[PDB]
Image: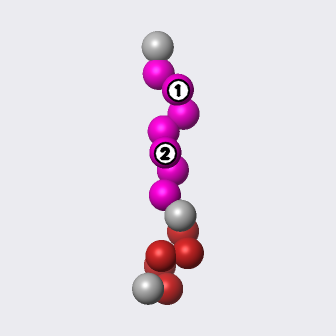
Amino acid sequence: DWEYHAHPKPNSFWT
């Protein structure tokens, strides 16, 4: 059994 992964914040593309 596996829950949904911790998908990253896409905003950091602009860092």
Callout 2: helix, strand or loop? loop
Amino acid at the residue labelled 1:
Glu
**What residue is pinned by disc 1?**
3
- Cα separation, mark 2 vs mark 1, equals 9 Å
> Given the current orientation, which residue lies at the most extreme top position?
1
User: Which labelled disc corresponds to residue 15?
Assistant: none
Residue 4 among those drawn in magenta: yes
Q: At x 44% / y 85%, what residue is drawn? A: 15
Q: At x 53% / y 64%, what residue is drawn? A: 9
Q: Which colour style is shown?
A: secondary structure
Q: At x 49% / y 85%, what residue is drawn? A: 14
Callout 1: helix, strand or loop? loop
Residue 2 screen position, x and y as percent: 47, 21
Q: At x 51% / y 50%, what residue is drawn? A: 7
Q: Residues within 10 Å of mark 2 (few under 14, many from 20)?
A: few
Left or right of residue 13: residue 11: right
Above or below: residue 5 compared with residue 2: below
User: Which labelled disc corresponds to residue 6?
Assistant: 2
> Given the current orientation, which residue lies at the most extreme bottom position?
14
Above or below: residue 8 compared with residue 2: below
Chief secondary structure of the magenta portion = loop
The reply to whether dot 2 and dot 1 touch (C-beta < 8 Å) is no
Above or below: residue 10 compared with residue 3: below
Q: Residues within 10 Å of mark 1 (few under 14, many from 20)?
A: few
Amino acid at the residue labelled 2:
Ala
Q: Which residues are magenta?
A: 2-8
